[PDB]
Image (spheres, coloured by chain):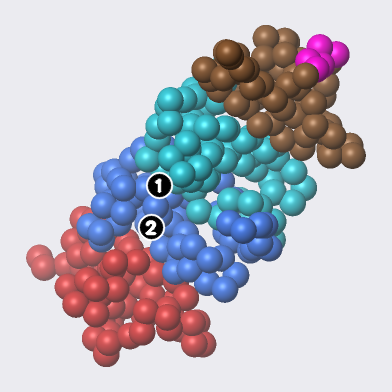
Chain colours: A cyan, B blue, C red, D brown
Amino acid sequence: IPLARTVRCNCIHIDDGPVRMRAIGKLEIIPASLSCPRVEIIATMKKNDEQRCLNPESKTIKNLMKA
Amino acid sequence: IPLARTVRCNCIHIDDGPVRMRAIGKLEIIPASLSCPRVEIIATMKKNDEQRCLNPESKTIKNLMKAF
Amino acid sequence: ARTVRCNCIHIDDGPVRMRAIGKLEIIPASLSCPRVEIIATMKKNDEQRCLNPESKTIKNLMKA
Amino acid sequence: ARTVRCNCIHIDDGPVRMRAIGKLEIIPASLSCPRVEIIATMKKNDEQRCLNPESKTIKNLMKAF
């Protein structure tokens, strides 16, 4: 809880409306790094392979992730 | 996202947890800027000075917001 | 007794550009200030001012 | 006829630290690949390799606390 930290991440906007394994093609998890002090979760929906950034801090998201 | 863009924002982690307007001492809304290309919404919970970053794209949040 | 201890002593009405604001604060009604308050930090000079919650330039603006 | 298309040819059972992982691309069990595939891209050389979905170095690495 300081000021603005300059960061470099893939995800800028984080999609909210959840889903389930059924619709998700691939799930890409990216561990926290020096450039992006947070985990990034990018799902590719079989629906036109629409890529969506999810919130790793979200309960549902956590549930879906770990199996 | 065509790639990674260098960005400078107040919010790094978005508490996509729940809430509503009991408590919430204050709610800050920072329009999208050249430095952060998406609006930030910082809530200062009535209790304990604790600050939470809310997802501006969250239906609940857009509705909690469009309620002033 | 009619009493009030709010942050705003002055309420702006002069319409303001969506892009001229740097920050916006919404402090909801309380016993100490039964009225909602919206304080904007303008980009220019970073001057803080209060906008009318009831105003359209605001209701429209509130589609942030 | 018939056909089967999994991405993995080798399954790295050897341990691995979250430290050296760039990312995981977890692919859900499909009709074409009747199991889940977890491809890791090591930080080192950006090397890709498959890890066993049912291995501990993975389950504990499956971070969420």
Q: Which residues are magenta?
A: D10-14
Residue at image point 33% right, 85% down: C16
| A49 on left or right of C10 | right
Q: Quadrant of residue D5?
A: top right
Residue at image point 53% right, 39% down: A44
> Is the residue C1 above or below the residue C50 in the image?
above
Given residues C57 and A40, the one toward you in this image is: A40
Residue C7 visible in image: no
The image shows residue C13 at horizontal and vertical percentages of 24, 86
Residue type for callout 1: Met
Earlier-in-chain disc, 2 versus 1: 2
Residue D14 visible in image: yes
Dot 1: chain letter? B
Residue indicated by mark 1: B45
- Dot label at residue B27: 2
The image shows residue C3 at horizontal and vertical percentages of 16, 67
Residue type for callout 2: Leu
Indicate the quadrant containing the C terminus of chain C: top left, top right, bottom left or bottom right. Answer: bottom left
Numbered disc 1: secondary structure: loop
